[PDB]
Length: 124
Ligand SMILES: [Cu+2]
Image 1 (cartoon, protein in one colour):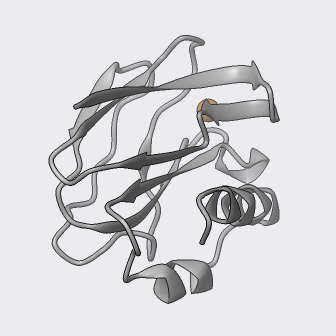
Image 2 (tube, protein in one colour; image 1 turned 90 degrees about the vertical axis):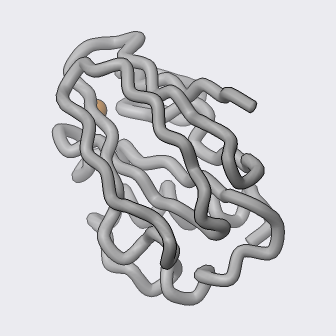
């Protein structure tokens, strides 16, 4: 199944957001990160991807489709706006096994606030 996450200057959660900021998908599903506003990218956060995955990094303004295969929780960031909390969480599968590793990953304060909230939104 194919899902879409927008990269926005403004959304329901404030400035510089992925919308939705939390998304649960099945293994083998895809997510397209859409440059609805310009100036953003999407890339893997360090320490917030499960074993079996591959890190990725899109270019600014690239409409970027990722197939998520390895079960677990994934943090993603926009590099331009990481410091502003432009992050998202994709959960692949149920009962993610890498929660404690991803909760311990270090992030800018605004990013950590948003990640903690997305994780809790997901019931983690
Ligand atoms: Cu951005």
